[PDB]
Amino acid sequence: EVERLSLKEFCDMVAERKPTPGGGAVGSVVGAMACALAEMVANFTRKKKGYEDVEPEMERIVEAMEEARLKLFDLAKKDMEAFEKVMKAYKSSEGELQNALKEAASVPMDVIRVMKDLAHELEKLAEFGNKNLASDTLNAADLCHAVFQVEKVNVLINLKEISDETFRKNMLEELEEQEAQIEGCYQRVKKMLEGIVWSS
Amino acid sequence: EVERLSLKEFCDMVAERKPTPGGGAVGSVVGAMACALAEMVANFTRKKKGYEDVEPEMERIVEAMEEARLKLFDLAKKDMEAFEKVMKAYKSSEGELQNALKEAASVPMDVIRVMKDLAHELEKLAEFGNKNLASDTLNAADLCHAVFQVEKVNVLINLKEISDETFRKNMLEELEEQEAQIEGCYQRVKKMLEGIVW
View 1 (spheres, rainbow over the protein chains, first blue to last red):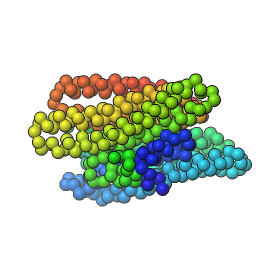
View 2: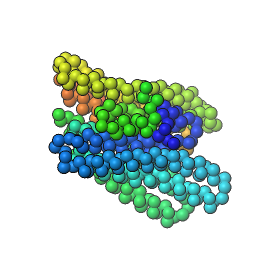
View 3: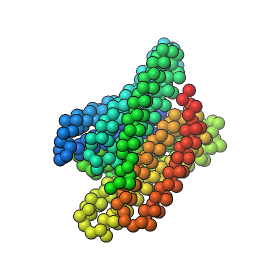
View 4: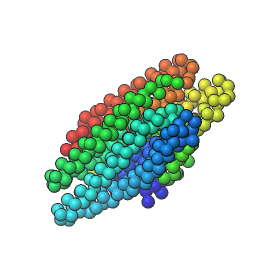
């Protein structure tokens, strides 16, 4: 579905006077690209002398980043579907709407979980990955973090419409935790890698 | 060229054991998508009652965001070309290499300047744009900011290799200005829009 879109196409659609692909969707797509950088760094670390005792770990990441893209591309589709379903219920019962709102809120939540995974891998890559691609790792950390920010906003815009208090308190809780994991990894990756910007 | 690639394609290539599309290139693509959000918000503000006296301004942003994307997609291509040229010069003269390094460092610098433009528009949209699309504006700002961070790294990784001091002090100087303009807009956009979250 979504991956088969060209970059110009996907953009034009975001740009369009339609609400179909919104921020959340874009976030997933960005996340997917961030996973690709992590995959690149992992690839450039396997089959490399000096990094052979972390090769098991590198092939493991490659495989995870492959699977994360598939998830993220799926979550972009869901985000657009979820939005249709909510909008196509603003005028139906409060039973159906409340439930649609829940599903919709779950989508960015899920994107964030993938981001939590990406962050943890970027931490492993910062530390054990190929030193000459630190830039690409850092780049991926910066995008990772933004995606998290994007999706957090999308999680909260949805929550505020949901009347079920416990569902809100829960999701908010999960959000809080994913945030901490992601911030932590992010800051560590930045701290570990900031020097590449001046040291050759 | 680049825009005609599918999302799966572009990704697979980043992921691939090749250095052709690197962070810098991703950054541009991301920036392009961020520009598209800004466009979306602008579109959803024109032809809207209550916002008619900012319509001239909204159509102006739509146009600018359209042109930004063309720039960004070009800069993505350049980044890959600039990297090839640099690598295919590691082993040639220090004349050729130094010059290749400068060109290469200009690419993300240029992407940054686009981001600076994006930031300024996001400031306009946060203020005058359609209130129910604030989320999209904010999302774009966060991406904008990240792209700047992506590209700054790529500007500096190149500079550090460039022996020409004045070129370095200049670039660094520009970089700091663009950073400040981007930060300022960013913070302002956040400050103005953070409240939509509750």
